[PDB]
Image (cartoon, coloured by chain):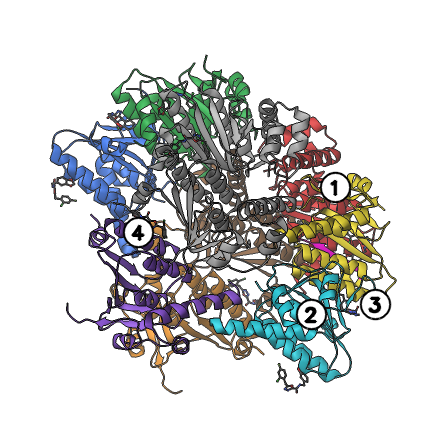
Chain colours: A cyan, B yellow, C red, D brown, E orange, F purple, I green, J blue
Amino acid sequence: YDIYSRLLRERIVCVMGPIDDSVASLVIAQLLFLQSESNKKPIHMAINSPGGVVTAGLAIYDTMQYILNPICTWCVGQAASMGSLLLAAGTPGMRHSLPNSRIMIHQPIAIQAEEIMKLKKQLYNIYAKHTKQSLQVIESAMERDRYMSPMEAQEFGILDKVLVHP
Amino acid sequence: YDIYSRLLRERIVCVMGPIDDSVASLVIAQLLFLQSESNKKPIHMAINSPGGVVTAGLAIYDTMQYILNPICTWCVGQAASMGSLLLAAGTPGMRHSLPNSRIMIHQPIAIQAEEIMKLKKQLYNIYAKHTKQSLQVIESAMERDRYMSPMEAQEFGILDKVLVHP
Amino acid sequence: YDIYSRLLRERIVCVMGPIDDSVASLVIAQLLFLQSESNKKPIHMAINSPGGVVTAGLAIYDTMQYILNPICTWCVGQAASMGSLLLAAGTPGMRHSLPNSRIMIHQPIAIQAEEIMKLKKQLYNIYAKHTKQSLQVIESAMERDRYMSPMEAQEFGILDKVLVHP
Amino acid sequence: YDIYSRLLRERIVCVMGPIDDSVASLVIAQLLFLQSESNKKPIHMAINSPGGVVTAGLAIYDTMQYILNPICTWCVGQAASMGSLLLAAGTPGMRHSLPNSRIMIHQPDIAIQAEEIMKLKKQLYNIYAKHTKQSLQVIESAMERDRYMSPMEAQEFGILDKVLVHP
Amino acid sequence: YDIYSRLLRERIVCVMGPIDDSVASLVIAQLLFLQSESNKKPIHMAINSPGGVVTAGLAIYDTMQYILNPICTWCVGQAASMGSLLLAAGTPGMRHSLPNSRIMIHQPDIAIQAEEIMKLKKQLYNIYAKHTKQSLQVIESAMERDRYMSPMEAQEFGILDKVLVHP
Amino acid sequence: YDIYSRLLRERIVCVMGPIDDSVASLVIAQLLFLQSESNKKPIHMAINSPGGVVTAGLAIYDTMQYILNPICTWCVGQAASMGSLLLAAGTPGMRHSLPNSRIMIHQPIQAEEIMKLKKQLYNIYAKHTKQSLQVIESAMERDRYMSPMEAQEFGILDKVLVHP
Amino acid sequence: YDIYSRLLRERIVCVMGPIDDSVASLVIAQLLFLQSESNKKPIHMAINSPGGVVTAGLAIYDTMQYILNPICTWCVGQAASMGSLLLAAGTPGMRHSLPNSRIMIHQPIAIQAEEIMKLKKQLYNIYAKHTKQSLQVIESAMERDRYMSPMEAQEFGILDKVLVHP
Amino acid sequence: DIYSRLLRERIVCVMGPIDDSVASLVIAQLLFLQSESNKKPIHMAINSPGGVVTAGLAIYDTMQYILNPICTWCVGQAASMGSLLLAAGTPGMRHSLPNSRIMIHQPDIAIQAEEIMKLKKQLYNIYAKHTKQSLQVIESAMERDRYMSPMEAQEFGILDKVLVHP
Amino acid sequence: YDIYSRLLRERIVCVMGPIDDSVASLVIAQLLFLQSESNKKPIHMAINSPGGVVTAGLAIYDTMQYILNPICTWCVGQAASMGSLLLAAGTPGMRHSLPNSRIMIHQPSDIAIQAEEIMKLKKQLYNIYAKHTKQSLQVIESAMERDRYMSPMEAQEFGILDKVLVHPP
Amino acid sequence: DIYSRLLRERIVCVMGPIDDSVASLVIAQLLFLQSESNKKPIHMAINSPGGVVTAGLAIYDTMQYILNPICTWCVGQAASMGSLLLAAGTPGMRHSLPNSRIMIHQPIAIQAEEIMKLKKQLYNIYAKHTKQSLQVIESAMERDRYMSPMEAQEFGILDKVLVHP
Ligand SMILES: O=C(NCc1ccc2c(c1)OCO2)c1nnc(Cc2ccc(F)cc2Cl)o1
Ligand SMILES: O=C(NCc1ccc2c(c1)OCO2)c1nnc(Cc2ccc(F)cc2Cl)o1
Ligand SMILES: O=C(NCc1ccc2c(c1)OCO2)c1nnc(Cc2ccc(F)cc2Cl)o1
Ligand SMILES: O=C(NCc1ccc2c(c1)OCO2)c1nnc(Cc2ccc(F)cc2Cl)o1
Ligand SMILES: O=C(NCc1ccc2c(c1)OCO2)c1nnc(Cc2ccc(F)cc2Cl)o1
Ligand SMILES: O=C(NCc1ccc2c(c1)OCO2)c1nnc(Cc2ccc(F)cc2Cl)o1
Ligand SMILES: O=C(NCc1ccc2c(c1)OCO2)c1nnc(Cc2ccc(F)cc2Cl)o1
Ligand SMILES: O=C(NCc1ccc2c(c1)OCO2)c1nnc(Cc2ccc(F)cc2Cl)o1
Ligand SMILES: O=C(NCc1ccc2c(c1)OCO2)c1nnc(Cc2ccc(F)cc2Cl)o1
Ligand SMILES: O=C(NCc1ccc2c(c1)OCO2)c1nnc(Cc2ccc(F)cc2Cl)o1
């Protein structure tokens, strides 16, 4: 009996490792499943990812917003690139992080020059929406190759609570 | 059934081999499971690791502090780099080691220079917290490429009991 | 069921092939398992190994000494490097070998120079402890790139009985 | 069920392909298993091997002699190097071969010194001479020739007892 | 159930793809099984093989001759080198072939000496002549030609008995 | 000596194949070389490239503009991506092409920097073809090749020659 | 003649492609050569590099400063990472750049955490010395994953003149 | 050829890792220059992270054997056996450029445990001889995984002069 | 020209690196070269080898003994396996070693041989060692059994080399 | 090049495995030395474990073709086709160093008959130059073993075993 099954029975979705179309398919499938069991019971999303494909990450993001369930996000280990975007996409008041985690919002098929900027500005708006920061701040922050502490990411607007014990 | 399914039925979590994001996910999943069965019954963590990814180790570490269960750590074979951190992070009075084990605290997507130091100082504080040593002592020891014996590591504050037989 | 799953029901643990951190984890779990069913019924350890990782072998060794069960060791095929150490680590009077086996005690993550030298003396003492020989004999014997016959290794203190038929 | 479990349910042990420590562990486990089911019912060992690791073969050899069961050896396809040694190690009167099988006794894990390889060679010399009832000098001179023997040829030599076309 | 499991319930053994010691072990194991179910009920051998190891092919051949069951051979797609030898080794009157199949008897373990390759070649010469009822002069001269035969050609030669478009 | 040296002795620089930092080093070295022998005699640049590294091409481009020699560009086979940029960067009135060639200006680091390079290419094309920025941007958006006469009617090259 | 045997006759040293220990030896040898021909005639260093090994760059830098010749640096194509350091290390008034070149000072054998910061602070001081900026400005500037235009680098102090034509 | 002219000025380049292939070349050039003049000094430019010990000791023994004075120059870095060759220069003629990195901590065929300590103890004596420090000081220093600045190595006794300009 | 073409003008043959049929061919060619030019001037052999193919080493050994020149051997860095055999095969009184070298005579465990033909080769190595070190066969057999290196002074007292030099007097 | 000076002394090196690539060079050097003088002898140094049969027979026939006397020298080892070239020297001029190893056992894709045709061709060539019977050669070549230089001299493969000149 897979341990990841008894995790699903507790409404926990693990987003660990890089994010590609294969990972997104599972996460989205698990999210739509838990919604059918209850569109009211909250869902916990554990994040330990260095990023991945943007479209695959945006696929999870729109799915997190589409469903009606509240989503508790937990940053474990690290949440970088698209991983921090999913972290900030949690239900307001339910975005958590463990004390020694690291948060990074800087960005490290084949597309055109105008297309990467379309996605980049598309990322600017999503961050500003959930962190309630200005577009100019997000641009300057994502330009810095740096990690943030859980307390730093709380001051930036990415997460709400840093917990040592429940 | 499978021997690894029986260790879990006996509240034993194996942290053996190198540590990456994949290993940490299992350990954290196994840790959260045993807590649900009982937030009072202790958990046994067997460690035979040469280290691994820092964020993955801090992920397990933060989870060890998060849960309420007492955690008995056992160094078998060796516990080096992030492995020694998990060993010293056990519940005080329950950090064990077998007689012929070796303990090493020296540290061997990329990051910037200012970021790895944010992690070393993050490791300095965690060691000093559980070994009850000064930051200068932890820093000075970690500068030496060396292993410690169970009795050597016991005086330093890494483990509490050295057992040949119970 | 599986032939190796039926061996476990007969208290037989197979240490064949090279020894690494993966082998030690499996063997230790089986040893801890058989002890739980009965701390009095003996355990049989079949050895056909050319050696392996030192720390992984010492992990099995400390577990062999830790538990209360008597351990019958059987040298089948060959027991070289760390393999002979586990063979000699059996309960006195229960160290066997088949007639055409070869026994070798000579030794063929990165460590420093002092630490591998710390490990050989760690091997010297364990051999000298179980063969009742002097350290000078063990040091001089391990200097010879050579194999011993089962009766020769019995003369040396590595095993007690050489059996052709039961 | 699995055919190899049906073979095991009929006391048949398959020694096919090269021999390494991985093969020997299974064969020894299957032999110790069948002895527990019955130390009196014979065991059938089918051999189609070109040889393999010497220490792994001697593990099977010592195990074949250790147990109390009679062991019927059947050479199908070929038995070379350690395979013929396991073939000749059967219970006298129970060493078989099929008509088109190929028998070879000439020899072609970790490294070894020179003295150890000659130790292993003389260890092979003694085992053959014991079961073929030939002299050691004959075995040494025969093993010097890079050659195969026919099933009938090996019967005159003492490696196998019966060459069967039909039962 | 696996289609290869249901095939066995109808006494069909599939010899398809190249022939090695691994393939021979399966075929021999399945053949011994069906004999236990019935030493009288026939066995069906479907062949779509380009050849393979000689000793592995001889292993199946000797096993086909050893057992008592009648064996129906079917050439499907192609049967070349050792594959055609097993095709001709069927029970007389039970060797079939489909219309668009192709049969080849021309030839393309450890490293073998020169005298050993001829001993295997002469071993193949005799097996063909026994089952095709042809002379050695015909077999050797035919095997010298790098060529395929039609099912009707191979029937005139003695390799198979029936060429069927429909049953 | 080497046939490519007797080409150099006649003021011919070959830019054929993809463009990397290695190609630019040779072209820049050969361009600086021919200028010393004579800052007035023109230089002939044969181009058969599908593109390459942007920075290496701009290195060649900036050097073509830097030197005082007139630059005759020749599109033979094809000139795509950065190759067409070097083709249009020739001295006005000296940009040639053979009849069966094909010219491509569509283009196959951080997002803000990839965009900085694209807009940087827009200006270089518009400068040498004398077309509007919207025209260059809209043209470079189409994944397609142009005929030698089309590239003349666009400002990329001046003459299409069958025989000298 | 060979063009590379002719660049040297004009006191031109090419620093193009990535920088490793092999490139530095060639560059250093050619620099030491040109000084012997004349310790007064200037040397021209063309730079088209995306960076490389830090120690290899410092080898060229110390050699550029050691020799007595004036050094004219030319940024053609790009000068990133260690390339921008060599560009700014030219003789004041002799650091050039072509109009479409791009300059990057952000930085994209194994070392320890304390040692990578020593190299970073070592890069901070070399940049600050030649650009006449504060250490605080350099640290924040090198933190931005971005390239600079030739005019930007002229204001920041990396180069002195931007030439379209001589 | 620049490498033919380097030799014409009595300069021997030891750059990159050190193997038997490098040592043979270096030894040949050293033996060559001694015949040209047993009095004219030889200049050794070193940019190495270390390598095989026996090859380094081969160069060391050859450097000491000949009668010529030997000027050593640390350029870029001199670590492991490279620093040993650096300190093996003629006293008063061991230089280093300001941004170099000197390391004395240690990271052809397999060797036994006793025969790595004999090499390690062999390195201790050579360092103490050429640095004029005690063996106890050298041993404790070589245990620290860290680099020294040229001025630090000047204070430690590895080199004599740190020059920015001559 | 090449620096290796300048050692040759000074009668120096480099046996540096592992030994295969390719290395032996050069050494054999270089050795016959220096003897034909002069059968009286000595030849200097610098050795920095961990061993190699046995037959290739015996090719150098038989060639070293065949020619008339005295041969000065130099152990630099290390001389292990077949390297020490060529080192000990130098003309008596002309076998050198630098102070930090490491000499090994234990053999580590171009075609594949049979079991009987490896003992024919080991005994072939035993006799050559005992001949040049003037130790007993029982000592050489027992010595080559120890997986160990010798110091130049250790290897001198054993009979492998004659002089340990820091500087030439 | 040292190998160019070797040719100036009429020495041809047959070292390493034998393939069509090695044979072409050796034959060219042999054809070269005959043009220089069909009377001055040629020295063939052999340190080979064998190789392709057709390449060896190509070298062998050329050794027999030319009129020059050919001195063969076994250094290190001469196995498979290497021993054939060793015995193919002019009688009385086939030498060997003391520690050399001689092996006569033979350890594109060809058919069984053509492979058996090649062995019998090797049987006859050995018997011709060693002056032995086919029965002796077949039985000797059947043993996977090496011979000493004195052993091979008693067999007829070489003439002199030299320690010093
Ligand atoms: O019926 C639907 N859900 C109920 C459901 C029930 C049980 C599940 C399940 C889903 O998943 C496994 O167990 C549904 N149908 N269409 C959508 C919209 C949609 C939204 C996001 C996305 F990525 C893809 C889609 Cl299609 O929802
Ligand atoms: O304990 C929790 N649920 C009970 C439970 C959890 C997992 C289980 C289980 C029962 O039975 C088998 O598996 C829980 N509450 N919030 C979270 C999110 C989270 C994820 C990772 C992490 F490091 C820290 C946190 Cl807080 O988990
Ligand atoms: O109750 C214990 N065992 C009983 C047991 C029962 C069933 C098992 C089993 C073990 O293993 C599979 O099935 C126990 N006591 N101490 C520990 C910690 C420990 C000690 C030594 C060591 F090498 C590793 C570890 Cl984790 O565990
Ligand atoms: O316990 C034995 N039989 C009972 C048995 C029952 C079920 C089995 C089995 C064995 O094996 C599979 O399932 C036994 N028989 N002989 C020995 C000595 C021995 C010899 C060689 C070796 F490698 C290991 C050993 Cl223990 O033990
Ligand atoms: O008829 C037989 N019934 C026993 C049997 C029953 C069920 C089986 C089986 C075997 O195998 C799986 O299912 C039989 N078995 N073996 C032989 C002789 C033989 C022939 C060829 C060979 F390579 C090896 C041998 Cl031992 O006869
Ligand atoms: O010295 C120059 N010419 C002499 C010369 C002579 C022979 C050559 C050669 C050059 O090249 C091979 O053969 C020179 N002319 N302009 C510059 C500035 C410059 C501009 C761009 C650039 F990428 C590099 C530089 Cl240095 O320098
Ligand atoms: O001979 C020297 N100069 C003249 C010279 C002439 C021709 C050259 C040459 C050098 O090099 C190619 O052709 C010299 N001797 N010592 C130094 C100090 C030094 C400084 C930095 C460095 F990395 C290495 C060293 Cl050695 O310079
Ligand atoms: O005969 C010699 N003439 C000098 C010389 C040497 C090499 C040359 C050269 C001139 O010109 C180009 O190359 C000679 N010098 N040293 C030795 C012995 C020796 C061998 C190896 C070693 F590491 C140390 C030493 Cl001392 O002999
Ligand atoms: O012709 C000989 N010398 C002349 C000569 C001249 C210049 C050389 C050379 C040789 O070598 C390159 O430069 C010669 N002297 N002895 C032999 C017998 C021999 C012994 C061993 C061996 F491996 C090969 C042979 Cl041929 O031949
Ligand atoms: O001396 C001959 N030509 C002149 C010559 C001169 C120098 C050479 C050479 C050839 O070759 C390089 O150096 C010669 N003698 N016989 C033949 C015919 C022949 C014989 C055997 C063979 F395999 C191939 C051929 Cl073509 O030609």
Residue type, numbered disc 4: Leu
Vertical relation: B36 (above or below) I88:
below
Q: Does the residue labelled 4 lie within 8 Å of ligand 6?
A: yes
- Is the Cβ of the residue at disc 2 closer than 8 Å to that at disc 4? no
Tags 1 and 4 on a common chain: no
Q: Quadrant of the C terminus of chain E?
A: bottom left
- Could you tell me which residue is drawn at 85 percent across and 46 percent down? B166
Tags 2 and 4 on a common chain: no
Query: In the rendering, at what x and y percent does residue E56 appear?
Result: 44, 61
- Could you tell me which residue is drawn at 56 percent across and 51 percent down? D90
Depth order, front residue of A50/E127 = A50
The residue beneath circle 1 is B100
Give neighbour class at mark 3: few <14, some 14-19, many 20+ (Cα, 10 Å). Answer: few
Chief SS of the magenta region: strand
Give neighbour class at mark 2: few <14, some 14-19, many 20+ (Cα, 10 Å). Answer: many
Q: Distance between the residues labelled 1 and 4?
A: 70 Å
Residue D146 seen in the figure: no
Q: Distance between the residues labelled 3 and 2?
A: 28 Å
The residue beneath circle 3 is B37
- Is the Cβ of the residue at disc 3 closer than 8 Å to that at disc 2? no
- Could you tell me which residue is drawn at 72 percent across and 30 percent down? C133
Residue F32, label in figure: 4
Q: How far apart are marks 2 and 4 (CA)?
A: 55 Å
Q: Distance between the residues labelled 1 and 3?
A: 34 Å
Residue type, numbered disc 1: Asn
The residue beneath circle 2 is A87
Residue B28 seen in the figure: yes
Q: Does the residue labelled 3 lie within 8 Å of ligand 2?
A: yes
Which span of residues is magenta-colored? B10-17
- Is the Cβ of the residue at disc 1 closer than 8 Å to that at disc 4? no
